[PDB]
Length: 95
Image (cartoon, one colour):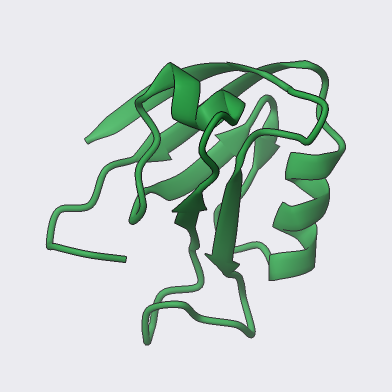
């Protein structure tokens, strides 16, 4: 299930780590970007909605679907302080 998350970029960024990307599949057969860690005190932690396992779809107007890992790293580092983060919650269990 798809949700939009509103984040202010903190001094250290959005407060979460990612894996995946085209050429760097986190899940076998999935080129998607996944949340692997939520940083305590971070903007993502404090908001409360983003979780380990979430799939990133977009960051503001930047698509994260079928992008390489470096592309998503850049998307997330170089956004505005006002972030709309679109994510999909897992159907199965994990990531």
